Length: 123
Image (cartoon, rainbow, N blue to C red; front, side, top):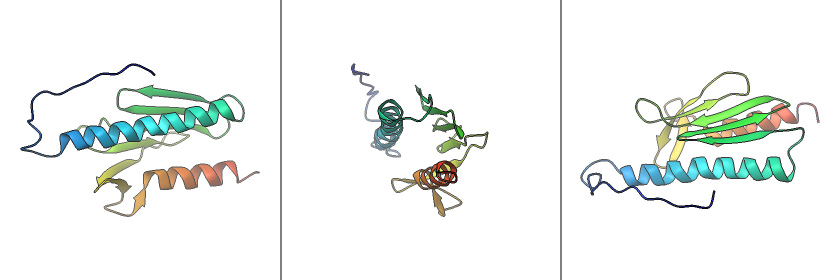
């Protein structure tokens, strides 16, 4: 986390779907996810959490409720949210908003509400 890179294989997206926008949002989305969790687990975790970042995947281990994961490297275009147990959520991109259920629920919404009621359920 400090270096930089680039990947421009000719303006082949300008004629088709907004590929650049997809890599920009998805890149910032996953990055911001592991960035916030990393700072929260390092600044004030709880027991011994672990934030891992993979190419198109955001692993987040939580030694209290389980392990949360969020990737977007499907055979098409979606964000899989691996629950703290073993339940990936296939979220679809919505004009810049990943929601599941043909437009019903949101990722950060289910993850924030789930983790909130999962960690607060006791505290």
